[PDB]
Image (cartoon, coloured by chain):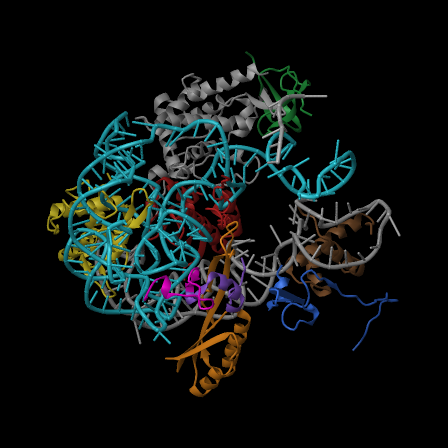
Chain colours: A brown, C green, D red, E yellow, F blue, G purple, H orange, I cyan
Amino acid sequence: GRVRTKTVKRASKALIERYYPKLTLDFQTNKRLCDEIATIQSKRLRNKIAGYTTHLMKRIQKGPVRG
Amino acid sequence: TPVVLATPIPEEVQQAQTEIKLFNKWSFEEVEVKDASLVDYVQVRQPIFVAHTAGRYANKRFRKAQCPIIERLTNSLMMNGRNNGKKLKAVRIIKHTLDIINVLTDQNPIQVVVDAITNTGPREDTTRVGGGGAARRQAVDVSPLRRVNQAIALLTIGAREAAFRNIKTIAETLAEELINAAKGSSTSYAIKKKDELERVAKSNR
Amino acid sequence: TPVTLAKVIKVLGRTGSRGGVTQVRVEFLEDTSRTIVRNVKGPVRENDILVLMESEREARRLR
Amino acid sequence: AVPSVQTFGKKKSATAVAHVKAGKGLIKVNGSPITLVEPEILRFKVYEPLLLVGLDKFSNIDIRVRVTGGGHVSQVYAIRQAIAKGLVAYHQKYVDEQSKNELKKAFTSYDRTLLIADSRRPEPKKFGGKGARSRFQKSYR
Amino acid sequence: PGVSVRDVAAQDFINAYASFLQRQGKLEVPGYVDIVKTSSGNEMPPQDAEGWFYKRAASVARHIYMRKQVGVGKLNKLYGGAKSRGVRPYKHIDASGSINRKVLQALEKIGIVEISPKGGRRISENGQRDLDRIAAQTLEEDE
Amino acid sequence: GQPVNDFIDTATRHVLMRQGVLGIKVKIMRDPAKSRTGPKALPDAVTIIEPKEEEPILAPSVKDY
Amino acid sequence: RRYGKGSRQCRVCSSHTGLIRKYGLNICRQCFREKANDIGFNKFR
Amino acid sequence: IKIRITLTSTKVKQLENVSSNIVKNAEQHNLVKKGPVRLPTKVLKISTRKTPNGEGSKTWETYEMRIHKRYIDLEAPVQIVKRITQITIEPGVDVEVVVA
RNA sequence: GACGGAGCCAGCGAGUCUAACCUUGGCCGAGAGGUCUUGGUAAUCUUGUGAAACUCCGUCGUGCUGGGGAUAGAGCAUUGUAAUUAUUGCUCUUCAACGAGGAAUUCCUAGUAAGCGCAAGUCAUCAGCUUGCGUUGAUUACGUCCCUGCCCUUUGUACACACC
RNA sequence: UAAUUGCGAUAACGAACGAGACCUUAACCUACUAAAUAGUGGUGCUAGCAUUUGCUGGUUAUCCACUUCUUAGAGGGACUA
RNA sequence: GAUGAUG
């Protein structure tokens, strides 16, 4: 199953609340931003963090996301 | 017109640029069988050469239905331990068997294999049903894909058992089995077994 | 005896003590707009065609 | 120098290297004609990439293959991948894009493995059995 | 067009050369052709008792033509098989060393092979002429 | 997991008392922020940099040189 | 004496059975597990 | 003056400090050299039962010690060769130098 | 399918100090094996570990038969102070049960089951065993809680060594 | 959801171990750094068949080039985008 | 809504 853990849910949330103007819907762009805006220990976890941040960005375009 | 190269490609092997024939003898345009229920589960619309594809069909539920039928009959001859694997014998036994069908009937050999399938898939079967341990049988319908599956198993189990401890070769007993079943002859192992299953089903409705 | 054909239009669930008996609803090819529910023994999808040996036997459910 | 291209194909451990250059129509595998490939029954697997696109395309070229590793069956599948790959890489560099695209469309529509390798690989054994998943027999009395 | 040994199927060439040498009759045959069996793995001596030694010579001739060098050991490896061992399972077992040594010593006395630097035997200029000449004939007989 | 090898030391000893032997095992998880060679934090530790304030500008301007 | 089970003993515990000789270790399987980390054999896969 | 300097260690990190030192030192003396040739890693496996007494389910365990070997070729005057052999001694890395 | 002649292809490994390891090649011998040399302290040589199943062309022809090779006789060799209660290998001869297996019961969802053999561990010699490795490669679900059990909630209990 | 994995609900609020992350290995890279103790091509010498500039080998004492196949070090790639 | 004793 593709459920995402709390480490991913919260690291992604913590980036949107500080970097909305700089984040975009592109995965490749977001992926490179998270190298300069965070210190993460692995390519795998970084890809997942950037992926879910992108996912939330689409949501915000449709309207306010809870929390 | 024929072409010649620095490496010669025999003329027996050059007409195939216009149409693919199984074992370079049999065509596919003329194979169609009229069981309207089984069209979407017998693959005779993608012509192949050698019946040795090495595809992947066990990763999704219904991908095996797209495998060409000749190869699914090949697969079922690799049975009973000492013959597991050895797909090169299966390809040879089906090369001989398709040949014997044409001689014995002056008819397309693949079309005979298809007819054997469509006359063996039992239409009604029975299931164990009970409560607390006490049980009985009850009649049910049989699905299209399983009709093809149980067809092949019967045709090749009878052909294997008929050749064992016999003078006749495997390609021959299978050849006779496929010829009789497509004719609807009660001599075949496949047809007799089908009627045994459907008789029981009617008595347990 | 005659044999009638029908077309699966929905797969309702699974039954039998061990799950080997799916439950389907069908629409008859000739004289369509008559539908019956009955049990099947192998893997099955929508738009499949089933050969019914007797048409008028609606099938019970174990639950 | 004359136009040249180097390509390869694999199946299990088998690998074949096909050198392709502008020539007269030679097709030799392991220093022998393509007509003498063994096992016999599977000759049409090697012939397939030629027939499917006509012998015409191969008249102006020379193809030399060499195989190692694997076994009798897996090597044959390595040859057929190398031959198909060589033709597509040659048309990439020396004819044009359209020809490469249309070629690729024919090869793929028949059998994907002609160009893309099979991703399957063997599973390791695990102690306690004779295979990756099988186990020794268990008894209770 | 020219022809090389590699242009003709192995089965045709081996029988063709074996016949040629049988007619020609100057190949030395070691005398025990009726007693010896070709390996410890086998249980019956060759079925074609008349011509089995000539067949073996043809196979080795082509075998050298393909490759640099060989030795009596390399041929034992290549002509071994599965030993029955009865109740116990099979195991590769090497072939007869005497037979393979006296087909290589015989092939030298006919001039088809020579000793080579780096050990073992090797084709000779005269060897290549004979095998190549017989390949072109075998093709001619495709009618 | 792997961090065990990096950040956990371990030892065990035998003490021969008069009643009989009795053993000890000591485990020390060193603090990873003080690591000198190797990873400087556990794998699942994510750090987000706090950006600077950035005010809107009044009107477009240019600079010469 | 020049050979056999009596010619070889674990260099650490003098035990005669279970000795492993690969790469000239000559350490009994029990003691090897204890000393494996120091010798340089780690557990990966 | 042909020389072949080889290296064998169980841990790559230290061995790349030594190798990178050698090549970068040689290029500042403009010597002619081969590249650092990396030979296949050879791994050592020991398989053993975990249990020290024979009871229980048959559980087997495997260990691994890894060996990385490299070599470079130099054609350089002897005076520079002397200090080269002397520098880059590091724990856990083994070096051997052969002439001609 | 057994036997015979041909065809002809792997990957994981190991190898010489307080010393005899892995062995190409030449020659003798039916065979095992013997002898003289040679390379390798190893991506260098043994080693393309020319492995087995496998393909092709033949002999036999449903006969406990050329399926099967137990149990026995006799001779020649190798390791070892020493093999008798045959350590093991070779050669001829002897040529039994076994015709697909009762009640029961084990393993398994794809390069997986299963067929086939190789290196390593033990080792002077001895693998029908174990740890890995590759070559050939299907059938059948894509489910359920019926049998055997597991995890969570509610509920009854005269159980606490706890349904034995 | 494979998961006390998450969405949420909430007399609870904020935390720790376990699962996940992590490591090892198997798949891809005609892109970087190199390499005869790995390879391939060309060229000196050379055997055979045909001989129009052809087909297949030998020569590791010829030398030159190159890195597709083989090796590793450093990186890329998948996050169900 | 078949059978299932004891330590």
Q: In which quarter of the image is residue G24?
A: bottom left
Q: Which of H52 and F22 is in front in this view?
A: F22
Q: Quadrant of residue F5?
A: bottom right
Left of E100 or right of it: where is B141?
Answer: right
**Residue G8 lies within the magenta run:** yes
| Residue at the extreme right of the image, as rendered | F58
Left of E29 or right of it: where is B117?
Answer: right
Q: Which of I46 and H20 is in front in this view?
A: I46
Image coords of residue I72 (percent x, y): 22, 42
- Magenta residues? G1-22
Image coords of residue F41 (percent x, y): 68, 66
Image coords of residue E48 (percent x, y): 18, 41
Q: Quadrant of residue B78?
A: top left
Q: Which quadrant is home to the N terminus of chain B? A: top left
Left of I7 or right of it: where is B27?
Answer: right
| Residue at the extreme top of the image, as rendered | C1
The correct choice, above or below, for F58 with respect to B190 in the image is below
Q: Is the magenta stretch mostly helix, strand or loop?
A: loop
Image coords of residue B118 (percent x, y): 49, 23
